[PDB]
Length: 153
Ligand code: NA
Ligand code: NA
Ligand SMILES: [Zn+2]
Ligand SMILES: [Zn+2]
Ligand SMILES: [Zn+2]
Ligand SMILES: [Zn+2]
Image 1 (cartoon, rainbow, N blue to C red):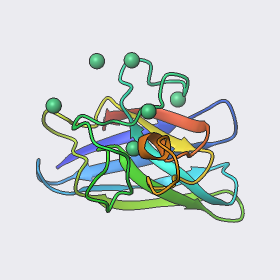
Image 2 (cartoon, helix red, strand yellow):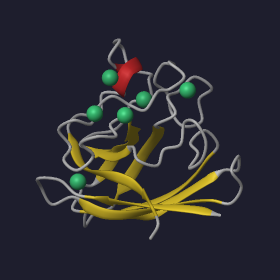
Image 3 (spheres, rainbow, N blue to C red):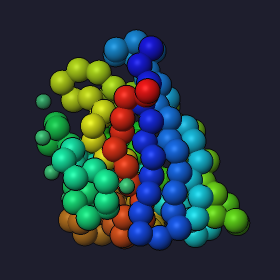
């Protein structure tokens, strides 16, 4: 199996450690971990295309979209590879991530390793909003924390 870790950091209090695992090179990817420092409620969770400046949040933003699709929720047929929906933070600001995804991969031509994991200020509207921007980013507001998806050491 192949594994990765992203350490999420930003300018504010949001931080977390997110794990990835994929048993077969074309198998589902499991994603898990906790993010703290969030406001209670839904927060957009995505893989950005950025693979150069993956440290800050400044250069991230455009979702990883190697197949030139429109933005959607993770279970939509039409979605970016980087569209991982929302995570939910509880009352004391902790969101637990538990995702199984069929579109991301840690191997091959479009591997998410090296790309930037991002947690955002607001809910991802899953591409169901009333403007073109919904179909690009889901209108999830500012990026609160991000980090490179690195191969596990
Ligand atoms: Na960072
Ligand atoms: Na964009
Ligand atoms: Zn490049
Ligand atoms: Zn770049
Ligand atoms: Zn390609
Ligand atoms: Zn997207």
